Structures are given as structure tokens and as C-alpha cells.
Image 1 (cartoon, one colour):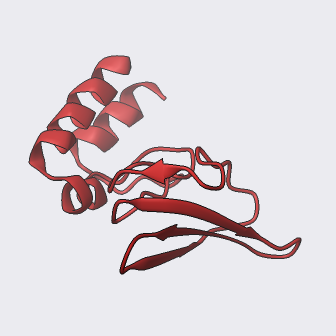
Image 2: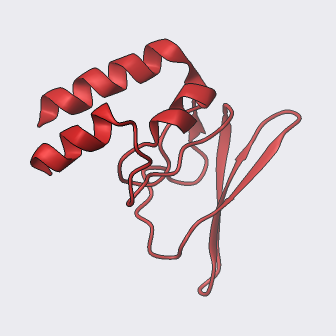
Length: 102
């Protein structure tokens, strides 16, 4: 994506084709009707229902364990959501590596 991707990173914009990340650690449970599609990240005392469009490529198959801040869909991560999910060091790592890819 070239120079626009770099600008999008240095400006910390929320990208348009944004991946969906998990807000908590937990276990995946896909719930796929032929009309709608959702992913649950469930833990001992928390349930996280992420309703996403039916055409989203998942990085996560049913039953996997995910860290808080791990991507479930494909695409670019919103840096502010990553910061809230996972903290400063992870956002630095992601910004540096994503800029260097280009």
C-alpha cells in the first residue's frame, strides 16, 4: 500500500479495512449461521460476542485460544484498539514493523 500506508501509520488513523481484535484473553467459539456470522471469545467469567460481516476471513478457527489484542479477522489493526487491548510496547512493536514492511 506504499506511501499511503506509511501516512496512515504515522497519523495513527483507524484504517478502512480494519481487522477485528479480541479485547480479552479467552477461547474461540465460532457461531456461523448461513445468514449471519459471529465469534465469541469466552473465558472463565467473561463472554465477548464479536459480530462481523459474513465475508470476513478469520485468522482463528473454532476452539483456539487467543491473547487479548490478537487479530481474529484479516486486515490492518487499529492502533488505538491495540493500545487499549495490549498496551504501549505492543503498539510500538506494531508501528515500527508495519512501517518497515513498506
